[PDB]
Image (tube, rainbow over all chains, first blue to last red; front, side):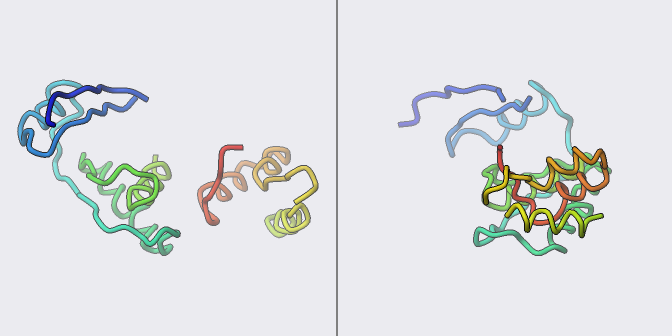
Length: 99
Length: 48
């Protein structure tokens, strides 16, 4: 059922839907060439969800001014979930806090 | 100035025209309260 691709940017973020088997390269070229942010200088992919409530304060402070500090210093785009309930909530708290 | 703030939310906490703890810091025209209320303190601010 891997017919086609059917979305674009919106909301000013730039999303899309794709399949699993698609491409290593044509994703990242479509990050860097089309709607290019930059090439990174690192990437910190963050994994591990909570049980639902708020994380601890010092883990929150680890993301507040320990990780996103290292993002704005070094480019360094963070690869997370995107949902407002997983770890992407708490990373999304940190980005919204630090900016 | 936050303890004064602390007593009012316990007072409004579910009838008296919901004081919301951040709408109040706006009315006092004190910015440093309104940041730390929104940046910290169990950050669960909803829409309304």
